Image (cartoon, coloured by chain):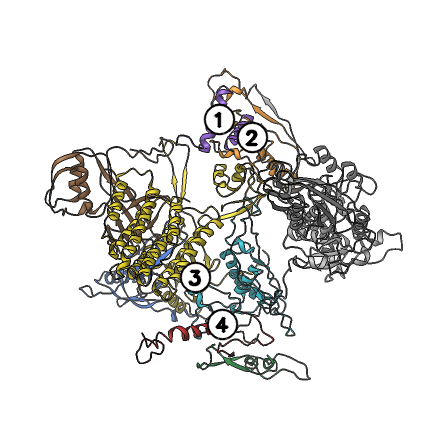
Chain colours: A brown, B purple, C blue, D yellow, F green, G cyan, H orange, I red
Amino acid sequence: MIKPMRIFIGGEELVTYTSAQLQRTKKQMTGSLTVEIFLDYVPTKPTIVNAVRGKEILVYIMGELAFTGAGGDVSVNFSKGNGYSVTLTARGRTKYLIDSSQTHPTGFFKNTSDKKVIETLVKEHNVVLQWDAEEIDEPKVTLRDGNRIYNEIFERCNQNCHFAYETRDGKLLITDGTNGTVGEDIILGYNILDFS
Amino acid sequence: CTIQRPDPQDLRNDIATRFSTNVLGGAPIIPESNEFYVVSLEYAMQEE
Amino acid sequence: GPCYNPDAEYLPASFKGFSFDADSSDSDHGRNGAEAEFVFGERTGYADLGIKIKSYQLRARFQTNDHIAQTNAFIAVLESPGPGLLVHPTRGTVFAACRSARVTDSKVDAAGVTYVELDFVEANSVLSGFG
Amino acid sequence: GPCYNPDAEYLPASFKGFSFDADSSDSDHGRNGAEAEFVFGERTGYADLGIKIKSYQLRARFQTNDHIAQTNAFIAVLESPGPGLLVHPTRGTVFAACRSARVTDSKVDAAGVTYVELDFVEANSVLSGFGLVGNLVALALAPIITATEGSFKRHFSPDNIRYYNTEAVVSTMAQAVTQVQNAYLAISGNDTSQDKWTTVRDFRNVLIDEFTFYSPANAWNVLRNGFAILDAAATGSDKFNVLRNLINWSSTHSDLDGESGDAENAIFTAVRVLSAAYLAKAYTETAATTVNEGLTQYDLIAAVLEQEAQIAKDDCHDNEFFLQIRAFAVDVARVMVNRAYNSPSLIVYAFPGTVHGLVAAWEIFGDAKRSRDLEARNNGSPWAVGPKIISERV
Amino acid sequence: DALSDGFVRLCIDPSLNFFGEGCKILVEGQMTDDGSATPDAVTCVTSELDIIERFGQGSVLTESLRKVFCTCKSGVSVYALPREDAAAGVKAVYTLTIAGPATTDGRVQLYMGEAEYAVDIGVDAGDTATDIAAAIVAAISPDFPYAATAAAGVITLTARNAGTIGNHLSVIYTNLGSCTSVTPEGVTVTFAQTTAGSVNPTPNDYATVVNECCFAVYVLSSDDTDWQENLRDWIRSAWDCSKPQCFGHGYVFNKGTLGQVLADGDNSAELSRLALPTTYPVLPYLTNAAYGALSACSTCNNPELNIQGQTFGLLSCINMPESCTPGWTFGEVTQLQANGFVVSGPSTTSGQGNYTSPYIYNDVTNYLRDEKNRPNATFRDASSRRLAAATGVALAEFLQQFNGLAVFTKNTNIRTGIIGTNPRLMLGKIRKWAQDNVGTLFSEFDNINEDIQLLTDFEVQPKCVGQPGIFHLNMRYRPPVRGARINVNMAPALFDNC
Amino acid sequence: TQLQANGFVVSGPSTTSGQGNYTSPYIYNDVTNYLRDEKNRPNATFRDASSRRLAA
Amino acid sequence: CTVDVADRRKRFWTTQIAACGTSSDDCGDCARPGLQLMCNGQGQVTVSTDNYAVGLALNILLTDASKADTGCGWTPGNRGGFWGDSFRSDNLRSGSKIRQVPTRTSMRETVSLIRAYALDDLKKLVTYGVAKSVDVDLTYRGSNKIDMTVIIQGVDGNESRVGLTGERISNAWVWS
Amino acid sequence: NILLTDASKADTGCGWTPGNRGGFWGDSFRSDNLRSGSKIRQVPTRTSMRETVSLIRAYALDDLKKLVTYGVAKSVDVDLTYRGSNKIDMTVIIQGVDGNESRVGLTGERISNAWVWS
Amino acid sequence: TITEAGNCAACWTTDHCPTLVDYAVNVGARLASVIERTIWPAVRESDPFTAVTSTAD
């Protein structure tokens, strides 16, 4: 079977998704799922809706996890001729770190390490941290008042080289090197549909 | 750890390389020839 | 049938009061809906989205020693503002609005006769402030 | 043929109830996929993406003294809202929706006949919503754990039992938590990350304290979280022996009387039911090697659950937990039976005489590298497997 | 039913099996006294569950039948012809001595007859020979055609049916004198054949029991060459020219050394001998019945299908352990191929031990010379025989349109309006039918102009002796040919000259 | 069935409703009481009540 | 263990031809199918479970399916079918509609219609996964009489053939 | 080796015995994406032996083209010509090269295994 | 018919034809029995003016 995906908003194995795009990246903290559902409407019978705006999903790609984190939005469209589509979007579980606002009481970490300041800037929204780089010590860590849970981390992992992104399980990976795991030797003339 | 039963295709590739280098002086194993069957037979022995 | 009287079964055509004789009568009824083609699935979906707008197609003939005057009067009527009441020969009275009227007229090939190809659309008012 | 009766072989066409006579009959079947054209390469790929939506095209005629009324009635029917049932003259009954119907009707050229060119599309019904299929490949352990929480907190209150038994009851609770701790410490093993290093400290900080288990809330939270951490430490077979030991530990009964015995028995029942549920979840995470094996595992778990239900029903202790256990038992039944019979569709191939592993694999599948797959299910020397060989469907 | 609603009224046929009742197979063999079926009278047999009660337990017939039922579940309807045992027949008795005592635990395994009679028991340490014999006798399947009894470590196997049919079990496959992982150490087995077979029935009454009761396949479960000769005479007289025909075909066997088997043959074109070696493990009539049943049950409406090959000629109901020597050597295999004998061999090469399944080469009849001593191969293939029968019946049904039709000889000028015909028009129609069946009943042809002749009786008999209406149709045909005889002439070419 | 045979109309209840439980009878075999012909030779020409109306 | 192979799946009761015996009515002898009760050695009767495929085919042929929508309608209780079809997930109907043929002249045409209907219905035997090659050979015109021989191609409980175009159906454990 | 070894049979609805479907399991490991053996003995026999001759020609030529595909010959060709009763003559030519490229400016490309001398 | 202890059963006259109908009779009578044994109490016992067997509670 060519079958790659099987999405679960909670257990409901999507069988109507008319299209899909799943993006993962190291340049950022999250990903971006984008499903397209049909959602018919018969204007006499009863109809049911799903107002998820937050109901959690995953995308098992080719019998293996690819994403983990319809939180993004619901975008029910309309038209006369090809209408009644529903674009669902779903960022990564490491999102509230992106759209929140730090609410730690003190604001002044003293004699701490970047790992610790990152553990307390995350465990306010239950995002287990996959620390796999090192422990750097720093005397003064004052967080700008309510800056953003993601700006502060990015600042604290850029002045000591540490890539900050998200894995397939739903965790925050703060690494310093690679994920190992070598693979296919793409050769020109063998599988590249296109290159640039 | 250390050592384990090898991937079937890797096992046969190594048997074919040994057979062609130490016996046939480096010649390729032309399919459907007697060396092809001899290599298949040796691979079967190692698999069993 | 064997004794089917044609001109006692087709209604005499006329648009916006101006009468004319028609030579054809078409229509484009229908119903528009979606078509779902879920990936990797032996299944299909359909969702009815409404009614397809009707359109009518006619062909008028003018074969009289004064077909030029009649053609010009017909042209003046067809270009009058707003929709008007149309008597389709095989669908009765509707409210239609002209959309195109081609007027073919040769001289050294066929003098005397003028043909007009008309294209109407079902035209209903709404009100003014969206219902 | 020479005696081909057409109207006794073509079906009379009709749409949505209204019948008419058709003049043509077409179809637009197909199979849509991609087409790969790797650059600089003498090779090409293809990927089957699904089913191309079917469409039918017909031509109806009306040649009757009242063809105008018939065509008007047919127009009024075709413009009805929603798809309806169509009788294609050569494909029988389908569900289609009209998409276009041109009505040719001339007078000074051909009066008497009216033609209609019809265009239908296979319109299958849908299920409003997100057409969300079920989940019958997986167990949901949330309802049974909530019911266990209820039945535990109902019969456990070390503040409402006789004073010469509270220390005994609480020591039994701490002993249960110690068992879960030992289970985790034996299942993790070579887990070096600091997450273990903390979880161990959390277990010790909970066990050393004295007033922690005197409250039903803390005790239940510790128990549920301990089982969840024990679950998340390994995958599948690894968690078998451990969990089965736990089922044996809590297979005892309390000698205290009245309310004290009821509290201790609540401890034991919570442990046994949580262990049965998590052992079911462990069985489901691994593939069945033989139908009898999957069915034997299901038999074990269903027996444990029925034993617990009989216990929770003995003299109307709690009717509610009995019903909850019964429901979880039927759920585990559906999932374990589907796993044993249908996860890989195991068939018994009948070979004439015993044969090698490679030859059997190549003849069944056309791929001899799959011989490794025939060893986990069949017992018999690698050079003589059979003469009946269990394997997967093809 | 009055309570129904519509008008289309279904009336289901009382019983099923309609598909069959055109491929009746007759199994003939002996029976014991336990059965309640009358001897020397054909009786239908419906299913398998009531043959032990009717034809005796463990008999030869209640064991062949069993294979006719195992081979194909449906497609045919089987008829038994039970034969009472001989008057002065003395049952053959083999014995099996077991010598211990045991020293280590293990299992005892034996293969008598076929895989359905196998035995597998458990033996502990310190068990004596008498106890092992007792357990073995208690574990032998009761359907094995050998009443087993025990005495002080000696097992006596007495044939249930008296005659020579008891002398065909001499390759018992034990598990006692080797190092298989499961082996009571200190026990040994010894085989004997104390007494031996005796006189066999010689019925010779087929005319009375089945006379106009046309069958398709006659299976014979005996080895007396005279009984086989009586069966052959029956089928031959059924393929006669005097009385209307009830075409059939018979399946017998012949077990022995090479010379004995080549001596047991003849020009018998109605039987298909099955040559079986001297050291065959399975009882012979079992595999004979399996072959006959497959042949009778697969070629019902396909009368050209050759029953031979690992697919179309596989006997799934026979399971042998392989043997160090391969029975017939290849020289003897070719020898038997030439002298119109069927040969069965193991399908897979599984190695010693290691159960297997036999299949058939050369589904041929025992026909190698003509009536005037002219070497032929017309009736060699057993499919050619069924094809000849089918073409006979097909031509007989085609020619029915001339029954009662007016015929015009001596003027051949049928007037305007008559519904008559004449010999030339009949010859044209017949010849068109013939070259219309090319590919299904006949080969291409060789010269259809002088192959089909239609003469009138008025020009065959002497003058003033013919009768009006009688005709004479002479046809010479060839069954459809198969295969080729390519002669490869491979030769390389190092030089090149484009 | 005995009544069906001798050209007798039979009426029975439509639904299976159980004791009590109002119902409504309907008719089976809308047939006439005609089973033999003239000169005593059995027939079925006028058995169906529609055959009579169609004769008229 | 090695003596494994025996599908632990069982078969429930099956309707059988002539289980209740024939019913002579001077036009012929029909079958009257029902449930066969097997006795034992000591009392203890038991319903038989043989011939599963023919039992399904009987349950299909001898059960009226929902009628088609007409302009006059049907009595609330005569519209055929089974309410239990509201709960199956395969999206199909239960029963046959050969008793609903719109009878017409030229009985050859009614023959063709009955063929179409019976073949459409009995295709559900292949669709459910119990047979593979059902087919009918309805051939007669007589006065009204008709023969309707039905064949139900089956398989065995052990795949003994390799390299098929199709697939082992779905339910080859009933033996078909 | 090619002519005298049975290739895999074609999938029929009838099926094949698990052990009769021809071929070689060793083809599961080669990398050139081909099969091993021929199928001259799998012709669907028919009347009018001219058609059978043409069929056997097609099969023999398709199977022997694997000599060129492997890189051992260059222009293998057959001359199957007879109809007789069943006799058939099938002379085969295997065009070869030498072990030293002695000709310059050829259209094709030296066989890859011209060291066997073809 | 009614047997000794209520239990409305089917009347197997000596021409019966075993089908599923009698199974339906069985399940209907069951339903009636389980109603009268489970819902009639627990509804008679929930009201202090009709309780019979649970006056102590």
User: Is the residue under label 1 in contact with that under label 2 (CB below 8 Å)?
Assistant: no
Give the camera-side residue of G124 and D231: D231
Within 10 Å of disc 2 (Cα), the crowding (few <14, some 14-19, many 20+) is many
* Residue D311 % position (x, y): 39, 61
Tag 2 residue = H64
- How far apart marks 4 and 3 lie (CA) works out to 24 Å
Choose between A15 and D220: the one closer to the eye.
D220
Residue for badge 3: G88
Measured in 3D between alpha carbons, the distance from the residue under mark 2 to the one under mark 3, in whole angstroms, is 56 Å
Residue at mark 1 to residue at mark 3: CA–CA distance = 57 Å
Q: Secondary structure at mark 4?
A: helix
D350 on left or right of H84:
left
Would residue A162 appear left or right of E421 to someone viewing this image? left
Q: Nearer the viewer, mark 2 or mark 1?
A: 1
Residue where numbered disc 4 is placed: I26
In the depicted view, which residue is nearer to us: D108 or G133?
A: G133
Indicate the amino acid at tag 1. Answer: Ala
